[PDB]
Image (tube, helix red, strand yellow):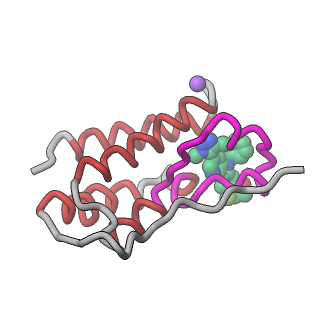
Amino acid sequence: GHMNPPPPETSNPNKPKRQTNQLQYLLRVVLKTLWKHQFAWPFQQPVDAVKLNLPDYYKIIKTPMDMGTIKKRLENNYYWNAQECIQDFNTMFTNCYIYNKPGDDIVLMAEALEKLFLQKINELP
Ligand SMILES: Cc1nnn(C)c1-c1cnc2c3cc(F)c(C(C)(C)O)cc3n([C@H](c3ccccc3)C3CCOCC3)c2c1
Ligand code: NA
């Protein structure tokens, strides 16, 4: 009846690459801190709508994003500007709030990670 879309692209080999203080901070400080949070595990890979039986997930969410994709993107120097990476983290949180309702365990988890994300991102060098 329903299948998953392909996961987001994690490499852009025809684009030029660079290291900046903000991109290193996004990988080694922001992503590293969120990845090891007690409630990070549902956000470390794309939503498997097939395994989780969510046939409406990819009908409601057209810009899926997850930390596993952000991690691979940062490791492949996918981002040239730190604001592109920040936008992917914000898309991941906004998708969770769009699909789910307050009081849902996944939302409580998302709100805790979002608080930690905002604390580290507000200190962006
Ligand atoms: C939905 C949704 N919307 N945004 N996100 C980011 C999600 C999301 C993403 N990944 C997982 C996920 C990955 C898993 F591997 C497992 C296993 C197979 C081990 O059970 C469960 C997983 N669930 C559960 C879940 C929530 C609602 C409906 C069905 C399943 C959560 C997990 C946390 O506790 C509460 C229930 C996810 C929800
Ligand atoms: Na909601």
Q: Report the residue at 20% width, 65% height from top.
A: 24
x then y, percent, for residue 7: 59, 61
Left or right: residue 73 versus residue 41 is left
By secondary structure, the bulk of the magenta-drawn segment is best described as loop
Q: State the count of labels.
A: 0
Relative to residue 35, is residue 54 depicted above or below? above
Find the residue positioned furthest to the right.
1
The answer to which image quadrant residue 116 occupies is top left
Left or right: residue 57 versus residue 124 is right
Q: Within the magenta stretch, is there residue 28?
A: no
Q: Report the residue at 54% width, 30% height from top.
A: 97
Q: Report the residue at 59% width, 41% height from top.
A: 62
The answer, for residue 113, to whether it is visible in the render is yes
Left or right: residue 63 versus residue 120 is right
Residues 36 and 9: in front is: 9
x then y, percent, for residue 118: 28, 39
x then y, percent, for residue 117: 32, 44
The answer, for residue 102, to whether it is visible in the render is no
Q: Within the magenta stretch, is there residue 49?
A: yes
The answer to which image quadrant residue 106 occupies is top right
Q: Report the residue at 42% width, 54% height from top.
A: 37
The answer to which image quadrant residue 21 occupies is bottom left
**Ligand 2 found in image quarter:** top right
Magenta segment boundaries in residue numbering: 43-68
Left or right: residue 124 versus residue 101 is left
x then y, percent, for residue 104: 63, 31
Residues 89 and 107: in front is: 89
Relative to residue 74, is residue 94 depicted above or below? above
